[PDB]
Amino acid sequence: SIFRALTAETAYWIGRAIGSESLARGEPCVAVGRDGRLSGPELVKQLIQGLVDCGCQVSDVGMVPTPVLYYAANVLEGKSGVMLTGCNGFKIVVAGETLANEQIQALRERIEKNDLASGVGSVEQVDILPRYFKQIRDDIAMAKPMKVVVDCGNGVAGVIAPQLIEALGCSVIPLYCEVDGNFPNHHPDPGKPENLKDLIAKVKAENADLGLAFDGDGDRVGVVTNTGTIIYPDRLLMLFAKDVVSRNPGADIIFDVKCTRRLIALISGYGGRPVMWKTGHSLIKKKMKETGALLAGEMSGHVFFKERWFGFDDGIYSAARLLEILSQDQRDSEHVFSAFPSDISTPEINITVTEDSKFAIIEALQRDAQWGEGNITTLDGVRVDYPKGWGLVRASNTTPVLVLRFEADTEEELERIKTVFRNQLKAVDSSLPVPF
Ligand SMILES: [Zn+2]
């Protein structure tokens, strides 16, 4: 069985465990959304039935982007919500908390151990999209008009993104904005440059001001400039953190261990409190609540606005917030972003190891490695920060792979940092293949 940190029968008892855990937290009201996945329409029935056979009062918001289901769970009567999505699958909020780790296992263990509530629940249809759409239109303040290419990769974002962007005061060139679970074009994953090539060509050919790309369910956004430069989430956060801290002195801003060190200095320089944390949407949201942070972001493309918003990751709202800021600058999006400091960085580096060894390699490094003049963070793998650059090694959670990133202000410092990591991996196992 798959229960991280799948057919009809699986769906029913997942809905059953969720309902039970929601009720145990004193929350009978649960919202339920699905993405564009082909199995969706049918499979949410089983999820809803699981919930109803608990006594839950379900708000069925139909086919929505993931952050619209999060919105529902913030705005409707109940603080519980379930999103059917395969990035179907499940993103779960119970009594305000986005579940993770030993919480999803606490659900599965209800399945096996038969620890489940029983009752006669309720289903209610709710049309949340117009309220979500209006909520954003009312708060966003666009100045100049902008031409934007929008790539939805045939995911569920095309139900609201091109429309909302047009409504914000934009001319939209849609790309693959028809909801199609078959994903007949590139799969909707703006993290991979390959998935951005159609968008880059389209931005250039149509002389647009910006290109935007959404993932399948809309909780991630990718950004390209009017000249086709891909703007990574860490550089995007630089722009957002500047704006957010400008109205909120001392505000905490969270980012993950893969983000450029430049973001630490930048946030501090504007009077904010930078907070480096672990990877993963659940872990970020949790830290945001713990710290009262106004903004967070992750290298995978999840951006979390609490300021003027609700604090969940929302690719569509983040697009809006981006459009708001760029519309207030006379410069093209290319120059707004290029004005920020830049360093030499590598792409992510993968080393295929084995499932047996991956975590042990990292623990060996945490125990045995020597790092010279370096600040060590072991929040998530081993990250070492030097005055002139930094390096990261972590174990992939889903694949038997070590993941590395390096950044430095110079070509040489890059080498000098890369060299240290190579040596420290070799001290763990001299046979390990270090492809850098
Ligand atoms: Zn997603």
Image: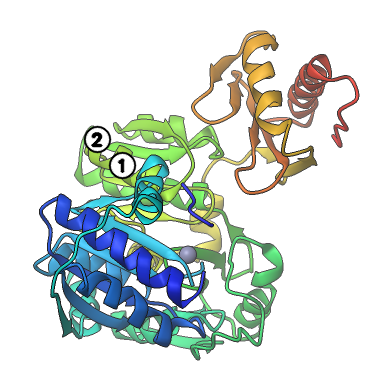
Mark 1 = which residue? 286
CB at mark 1 closer than 8 A to ligand 1?
no
Q: Is residue 402 above or below residue 49?
A: above
The amino acid at mark 1 is Lys
Callout 2 touching callout 1 (CB < 8 Å) = yes
Q: Relative to residue 154, is residue 340 depicted above or below?
A: above
Packing grade of label 2 (10 A; few <14, some 14-19, many >=20) is few
The scheme the figure's colours follow is rainbow
Cα separation between marks 2 and 1: 6 Å
The quarter of the image holding the N terminus is bottom right
- Counting other residues with Cα less than 10 Å from the Cα at mark 1, is it few (<14), some (14-19), or many (20 or more)? some
The answer to whether residue 427 is left or right of residue 168 is right
Instruction: Give coordinates of residue 194: x percent, y percent.
Output: 71, 68
Query: Image quarter for residue 51?
Result: bottom left
SS of the residue at dot 2? helix
Q: Which residue is mark 2?
A: 290
Comparing 431 with 357, the one in front is: 357
Q: Residue at x 18, y 77 (%)?
A: 59
Residue kind at label 2, given as amino acid type: Glu
